[PDB]
């Protein structure tokens, strides 16, 4: 029993992290097969970042200007290309520790583990969600760019995120591993305001089911609701709308606990309207939205 | 910027996890050099667990009764001994992935990462604290016993915990890697009530400093206090007493932020007396006590 904000074991990803230096800029790269993936802003001075023309900056760069270090061994760069906002450095050595992997573009509300790295070296691992405004709330200091977000399905790492940017409001923006930003963000030091950080309703409901499964039941009430009624209350509280797709996804948890999804919606409705009155659910004083329904089933069943 | 509940990268520990089977019981073992460490209750039926005589149960066991599997390869057991509440299975092969390591017995309030494992296979990693009542609040299903808690200092894994027990109240109890329980707990299925789960005051203060460093400053007030005055309020709120040792440990964070420790105590005092009034600190609606001062400095500086 017990329910924790749990990251994927990071070993398979630790084995892929390298240091990339271009001039005076050092950040992290991801070494998969004979390609190293890193943010294209590795080629920028902090001055460049105000208004960079990446194509023009890149013309001035040769293979030998990209210093790639894996542990304390240098990799030989034999090619480089820009794909969207990432550089692909071709090296002459396939990473011997390359796991089975995929590049996936996640949807808002989807969760993933981040391996925070500095100078190609892992500092820690934590669990994130892609926010509905396509920001993440991470822990990223200077040097952390090129740190990656991932899911693991048994032995296959799905890479979904590479860290590029802290917005002036201290939230985080990055790309998939094709170098396309999540949301409307750009790799430029400019006014970039995030939109409304709404609560991921389906995730909150999953976590309420996790709470019931783990003995925290005080918030269960005698009420039910409808999707339309619930959604009026959700809108008012800056909660994402709940769809029949979300109800379907919660079916297995509904089944396991014998609490109909719409009954759990009615519990959530009362919690929104009445608050926690100083009580906690799974050691939280607020409604937790960084567990997917899949996360709750995985952790409640013990998948490896 | 940003501050996350962050675990150590788990790769070095993933490389040490094996499956141990004795009869119908499968749990996890830790393979370091040519020794596999596992909970001695691997030799118990669920019936045995009501009132086990471990010495008598062990007499009936031979090396060949301990099935040790590392990935899909069997290890040959060439010796076995009981040390306190752990078994040490001597195997004929040193673990090739053995990291530099130490066995440490942590104090209450100290934090560590758990690698949750089932059948010798990692499912996830999360950050814990040893509670002042010598319980931990983990995520441990059946099969998770032998999962370990650790700290990493650069390249040296300090193992501090091995999972043994869920108490009837759903909190967790285990041993150091010499097999000595934290607190008064025993590996017997019996009435074992935890004492008062007090808040780790020095950790809350560290996290308030982390909040200031990360721009969350709304709780800073115009007041100061004394250790004795603060401690009267702490006692009332089931907070651990604050000692001059704790004040000293917070010195570097005091220095960095220019907030005297006793001023931060006076902020914490008001938060205890007034509550959060529906506000959050680093995305928490309650005062977080699972970051040590060392944790806050590590994460705020980017140690790898
Ligand atoms: O399940 C919720 C938690 C718990 C509570 C009691 C026992 C064990 N675990 C609290 C915070 C995260 C883990
Ligand atoms: O620092 C606190 C958190 C944050 C908030 C804003 C931006 C980035 N990170 C919220 C929860 C954990 C991370």
Image (tube, coloured by chain):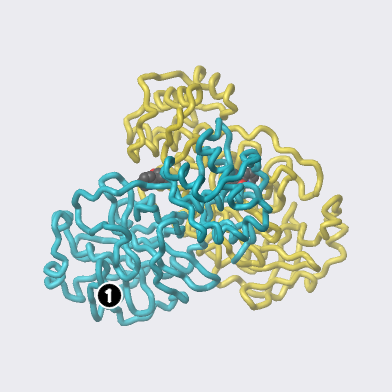
Chain colours: A yellow, B cyan
Numbered label tally: 1
B200 versus B155 height, above or below: above
- Quarter assignment of residue A59: bottom right
Left or right of A159 on screen, residue B177: left
Residue found at x 25% / y 69%: B84
Q: Secondary structure at mark 1?
A: strand
B119 versus B238 height, above or below: below
Q: Can the viewer see residue B111?
A: yes
Label 1 CB less than 8 angstroms from ligand 1: no
Q: Can the viewer see residue A203?
A: no
Residue found at x 34% / y 63%: B162
Left or right of B162 on screen, residue A153: right
Where residue B245 appears, as percent x and y from the top left, is 51, 61
Q: Which residue is mark 1?
A: B89
Q: Dot 1 surroundings within 10 Å: few (below 14), some, or many (20 or more)? A: many
A17 versus A112 height, above or below: below
Residue found at x 52% / y 27%: A242
Say which chain tag 1 marks: B
Where residue A201 appears, as percent x and y from the top left, is 52, 31
Left or right of B128 on screen, residue B81: left
Question: Which one is in front, B5 or A231?
Answer: B5
- Quarter assignment of residue B301: bottom right
Left or right of B48 on screen, residue A136: right
Where residue B61 appears, as percent x and y from the top left, is 15, 72
Residue found at x 55% / y 43%: B268
B157 versus B91 height, above or below: above
The quadrant of the rendered image in which ligand 2 is seen is: top right
Question: Which one is in front, A160 or A119?
Answer: A119
- Quarter assignment of residue B247: bottom right
């Amino acid at each position: 029993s017990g329910f924790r904000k749990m990251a994927f074991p990071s070993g398979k990803v630790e084995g892929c992290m390298v240091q990339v230096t271009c001039g005076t800029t050092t950040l992290n790269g991801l070494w998969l097969d004979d390609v190293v993936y890193c943010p294209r802003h590795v080629i920028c001075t902090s001055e460049d970042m105000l208004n960079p023309n990446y194509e023009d900056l890149l013309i001035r760069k040769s293979n030998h200007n990209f210093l790639v270090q894996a542990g304390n061994v240098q990799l030989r760069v034999i090619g480089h290309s820009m794909q969207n906002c990432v550089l692909k450095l071709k090296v002459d050595t396939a990473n011997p520790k390359t796991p089975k992997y995929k590049f996936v573009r996640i949807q808002p509300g989807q969760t993933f583990s981040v391996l925070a790295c500095y100078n190609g070296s892992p500092s820690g691992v934590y669990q994130c969600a892609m926010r509905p405004n396509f920001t993440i709330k991470g822990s990223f200091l200077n040097g952390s760019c090129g740190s990656v977000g991932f899911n693991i399905d048994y032995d296959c790492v799905s890479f979904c995120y590479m860290h590029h940017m802290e917005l002036p409001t201290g939230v985080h923006a990055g790309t998939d591993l094709e170098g396309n930003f999540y949301g409307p963000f750009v790799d430029r030091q400019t006014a970039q305001a995030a939109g409304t950080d709404t609560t991921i309703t389906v995730n909150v409901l999953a976590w309420l089911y996790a709470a019931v499964i783990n003995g925290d039941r005080w918030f269960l009430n005698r009420f039910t609701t409808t999707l339309n009624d619930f959604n009026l209350v959700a809108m008012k509280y800056n909660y994402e709308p709940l769809t029949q797709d979300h109800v379907d996804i919660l079916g297995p948890l509904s089944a396991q606990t014998g609490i109909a999804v719409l009954d759990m919606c009615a519990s959530l409705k009362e919690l929104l309207q009445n608050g926690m009155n100083g009580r906690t659910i799974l050691g939280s004083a607020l409604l937790e939205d960084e567990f997917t329904p899949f996360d709750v089933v995985r952790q409640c069943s013990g998948v490896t």
